[PDB]
Image (cartoon, coloured by chain):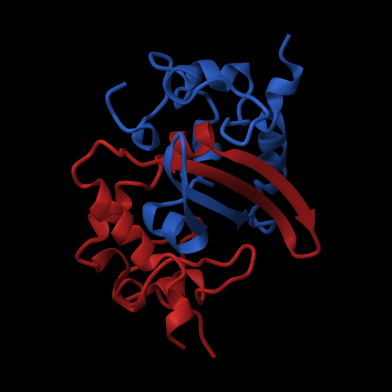
Chain colours: A blue, B red
Amino acid sequence: SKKPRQKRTATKAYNVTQAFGRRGPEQTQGNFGDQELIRQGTDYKHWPQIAQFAPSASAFFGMSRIGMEVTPSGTWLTYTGAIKLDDKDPNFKDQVILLNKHIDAYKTFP
Amino acid sequence: HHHHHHSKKPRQKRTATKAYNVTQAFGRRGPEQTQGNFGDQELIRQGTDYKHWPQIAQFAPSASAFFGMSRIGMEVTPSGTWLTYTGAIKLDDKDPNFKDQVILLNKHIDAYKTFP
């Protein structure tokens, strides 16, 4: 689409591959999403349960380690971090199952 | 003796402001592996009330982009279960504002090294 990559929202009409590229093993590639989530984006039935872990803009810049890398491909704002699950949430076990369904799911794609 | 009165939201959903600053919401800036390193004294104190916040927030990802672009993992450790993330967001080097964006981001990256 015409938006900067980081502001795109994937849906059935403009899916994860279209917005964010194929899943893969490279540092530059995303690794998250089974075939259903890839094709459906935010239309995926359990999208809200995934999105609850995504950071607000304030938390993205507040929690992460932020860097800047200048490479031949361009200038990149790098980010890394970790978000703790609330194991006192009764939904904790469902959250673990859901994340396990999508993290590196492309390793099973035919 | 207390938790901050604005701390009810999960950490990743918090919004820092003058009333709930970056240190209060997200911890002291520092060098350690999962510790935040971003913000000068003005941004730390003001959070999203910082007058140039929109020019920083233009680089933050939507929830869909966060899960679509990043490398996501999960780790179970003695402290709990953690969703790990890494990624990179490309700046538009053809934007006339590009040089100013770089200056603004660099002003905040590791700024904590220069003050107590």
Q: In the shown orientation, is residue B15 left or right of residue B81?
A: left
Residue A75: image quadrant is: top left
Q: Is residue B42 above or below residue B100?
A: below
Residue found 62% across the figure and 63% down from its top: B34
Q: In the shown orientation, is residue B3 left or right of residue A75?
A: right
Quadrant of the frame with the N terminus of chain B? bottom right
Residue A104 locus on image (x, y percent): 70, 30
Residue A26 locus on image (x, y percent): 64, 31
- Choose between A100 and B93: the one closer to the eye: B93
Residue A49 locus on image (x, y percent): 55, 38
Residue found 29% across the figure and 29% down from its top: A3
- Choose between A27 and A46: the one closer to the eye: A27
Q: In the shown orientation, is residue A44 left or right of residue A103?
A: left
Residue A27: image quadrant is: top right
Q: Residue furthest bottom?
A: B1
Q: Residue furthest top?
A: A110
